[PDB]
Structure formats: C-alpha cells, structure tokens
Image (cartoon, helix red, strand yellow):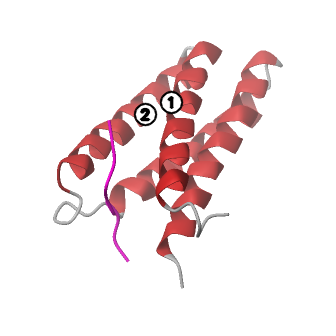
Amino acid sequence: YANAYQAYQHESPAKLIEMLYEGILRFSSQAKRCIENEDIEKKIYYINRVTDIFTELLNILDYEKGGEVAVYLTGLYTHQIKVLTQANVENDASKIDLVLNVARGLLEAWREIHSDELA
C-alpha cells in the first residue's frame, strides 16, 4: 500500500503529520460515540474537524517527490471525506470504523518510518 517515502511539503516536519493523523483518530472516535448517543450537533462538530484535517492533508501533498504514493493518498483522502459525509448524513458508525482503521494504518506506517523521531 505505502513505503520508502516523504509524500508531504514544508525542527521536524514528521511530528506535524502525526498530529493530524492523531486528530483524525481522536475526533473520529469521539464522532462514533456521538452517533451511538444520538448527539447530532456534537457529531457534525467532530466530523467537520476530521474533514478539515483530511482537507489539510490534501493541500500539503507533494506530487513531485511523493510519486505514486502521493497519487494513492489523494485517493485515500478525497474518498475518506466522502465516506465521512456518508457516515454523517446516514448516521452509520460501521463507516467511521472504516476511517479509523484507515488512519491507524497510516499512522502506524508513518511511525514505523520515523521510529526514532516520533517516540
């Protein structure tokens, strides 16, 4: 799926990505809670934050240096937004699980590559 790369643009750039991926995990997880408890207001909050992140993640991708894996993430992220909008509109928690599983894999991989730095 993904290895041997720096696929983003712009003292430690890697930690920044971890924070964004953690934000997704966190808010997604909080958003799941909210679907279960039926707090709609709180859910729209927590989704829009996850969305804002993927949107950030999309804007700082390097198509030059990131190659095929930059192309793959553009796919991953824009899909992830669509999936998020669906989970929102149609109130599906299995769906937030899909996004969560996704950010976990990314984050695990990202930490694997920056093992010493992200300790």
Magenta stretch: residue 7 in it? yes
- The answer to whether the residue labelled 2 contacts the one labelled 1, judged by CB atoms less than 8 Å apart, is yes
Q: Which residues are magenta?
A: 1-10
- Residue 71 is left or right of residue 10, and the answer is left
Percent of width and height locating residue 9: 34, 71
**Residue sitting at 60 percent across and 14 percent down?**
94
Q: Is residue 90 visible?
A: yes
- Per the image, label 2 sits on a secondary structure element best described as helix
Answer above or below: position of 80 versus 10. Answer: above
Name of the residue lying farthest toward the front: 116
Q: CA distance from mark 2 to mark 1?
A: 6 Å
Percent of width and height locating residue 44: 65, 35
Q: Which residue is mark 1?
A: 84
Answer above or below: position of 67 versus 71. Answer: below
**Residue sitting at 33 percent across and 63 percent down?**
6
Write down the quadrant of residue 64 in the picture. Answer: bottom left
Percent of width and height locating residue 96: 59, 25
Quarter of the image with the N terminus is top left
In the rendered structure, which amino acid carries the disc numbered 2? Gln
**Residue sitting at 55 percent across and 54 percent down?**
111
Q: Main secondary structure of the magenta part?
A: loop
Q: Which residue is mark 2?
A: 80
Percent of width and height locating residue 77: 38, 41
